[PDB]
Amino acid sequence: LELDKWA
Amino acid sequence: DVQLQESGPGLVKPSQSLSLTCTVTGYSITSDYAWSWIRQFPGNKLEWMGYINYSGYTSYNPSLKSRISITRDTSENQFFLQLHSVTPEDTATYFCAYGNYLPAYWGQGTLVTVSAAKTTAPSVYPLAPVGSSVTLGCLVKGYFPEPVTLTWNSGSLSSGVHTFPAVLQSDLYTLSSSVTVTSSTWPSQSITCNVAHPASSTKVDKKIEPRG
Amino acid sequence: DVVMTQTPLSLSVTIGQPASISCKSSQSLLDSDGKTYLNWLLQRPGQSPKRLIYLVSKLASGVPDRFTGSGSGTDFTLKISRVEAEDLGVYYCWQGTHFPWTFGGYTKLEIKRADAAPTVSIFPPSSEQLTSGGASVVCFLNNFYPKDINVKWKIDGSERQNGVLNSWTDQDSKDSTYSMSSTLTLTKDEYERHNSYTCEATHKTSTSPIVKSFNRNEC
Image (cartoon, rainbow over all chains, first blue to last red; front, side, top):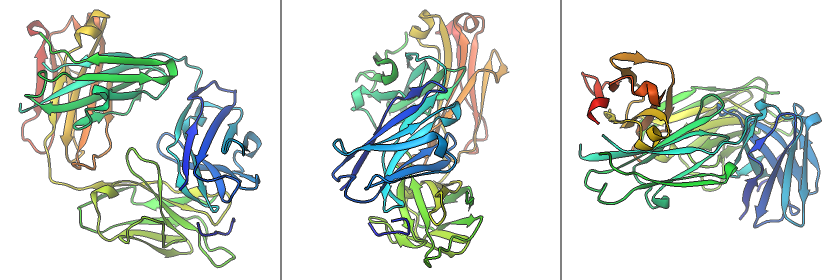
């Protein structure tokens, strides 16, 4: 899974 | 890939605390990602409750913070929802999910009812008819809480089946299910309604007998 | 919390035709990192919710190209170029730019099909419910469209509105029809004080109401 801002 | 599977008490008394388990398979919750709890209220509104990440760091919806905790057991590859001071308004379908961190995959969900009403096993009644097709019915009456599981011929009859959502009348649920077959299929081939109510450990098999 | 509003709440579309949903947020979803964390979620009847779109327009794995997301700031759109039956379900837009993440009010997509008259079936109280001293009369209205329908219970010719439980299945992706259950709950003794039990359904597929009826003194 691609990283979003929260990761 | 990853499987998520929710479990827990379907009924909790008001003012007590709710406890749910999400069992994860195919991937360690310690490897990566954020593991969330999300609930869907009657009427279908969705609320994100909080997550625990792979490191054990948590984040909670401010609306629930003073009331909620999410924990885990790395040996069992499970994470848990704990919700305190519950009220009937906390009645909902609880889903676990995971993402990075935004949820990408969801579990099946588990129903949790918050109420003082007592557990009641259902009465199950066969509905036999009085065209080219013939419709048979099953009436599941006066049970609590949700849900029940209903099948026809132990699940071997799935086509032409309509199972209607339970309606709450006077602190008791009523549900019905219909099955439509060819007029020359029944009663020559027997049809039976199977109803399970886990809450009361009930399991009934009621055959649809033709009327006089 | 950021409020997400969807339009329309209801969508009726023919197979092969385009469908679209609008989503609006109470404040800009554009993050300081330059990206906009706007998501779309689909919940089909009898299935777990499923991710369709993230970051406004990025397609989740397994999601057909037919689905297309766009928009910016506070205004967003989900478009399905070619609707299939499997597309029926409930659609949610939700934002992940601001904490806490919040969901919009759903849009229900129904598959518009040709009109179909209800198969109406009436059921006297089961010989088992009666012996136990109960009396429910049930009417199934199966496999019809559109959803618009009028169902009346008449006991000895008198319309009944108290104790009538009506329940609907979700639209069936197999035939695009609806079914509804209508139940009138009486007591063993009240059931025995009346004779005629009638389920009357009004639907645009018929000029005359569809009537199913039985008389106690004939069973």
